[PDB]
Length: 178
Length: 148
Image 1 (cartoon, rainbow over the protein chains, first blue to last red):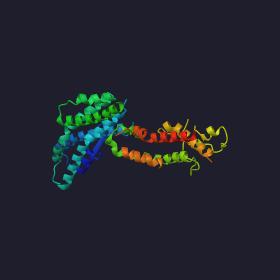
Image 2 (image 1 turned 30 degrees about the vertical axis):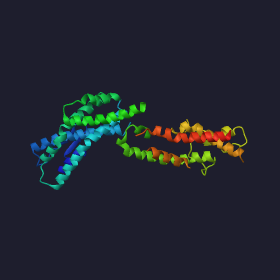
Image 3 (image 1 turned 90 degrees about the vertical axis):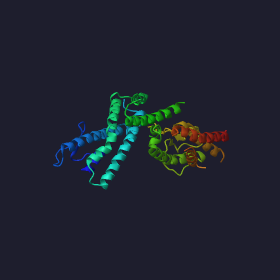
Image 4 (image 1 turned 180 degrees about the horizontal axis):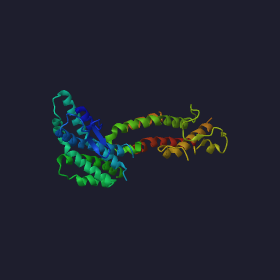
């Protein structure tokens, strides 16, 4: 269960964990041991799993291929990947500690991933705003800067990191043009 | 691809340096061919992998030897981007050395490699502008002066 759980968090849904394309990641509530609290935690985690899935889709869309196009968009995808990286490292460490002690409760995993539980929805909000408005070019640099003054210290740090990446790209541009 | 990945920075440096090395390898044979064509004018080659078609049937002592000796590969036309700026210089340099040899009867790949190693981030287009072309300019002017 736990390994399937993390692999679904790893972007690889299993049999119980079903990924509807726009229905998100959801729980095949069929196991005889599942409990309402169990399923509620499962849904809370499938939230972040769907977030990661959509992140991966977007980044593949606008980093592996050249409206929705330009160096700004590739940099956005790269910085989003970098920001999600510590989430992946935390996931791997949690897997390791489960592989060490089998008496660990899924509640422990939820405790651990609460660090990104709040972080992820803000990032999804930002990226969905960027896509829907089709923000392109240096406008995107302003966009996150608008959101760069947010009230979520975790989200704010992630936004500062991505904004520094954007600053670096546009500094490359400005150095070239100067 | 290398031009499009210049602006990413060192975030994709794993890909950036890989593509740099690959392009260096791919272009070395062209460097060697151009060098041999403009140092001697013959090749150990028999059908070329090179853009400009060679008309080997042009008589040496003939007016169109200045023209027909090398034939542009028009389909529109086969060409490579970084080769475009020096294409004319290449053509005149090679034909000039050929004429000088007619009237008188280190490797550029290595130079490019050492230049790019000394220099290497920086625009690879500007990298090439800085390193590659000056060698061609010097050789072209030297050949022109000798011929004249």
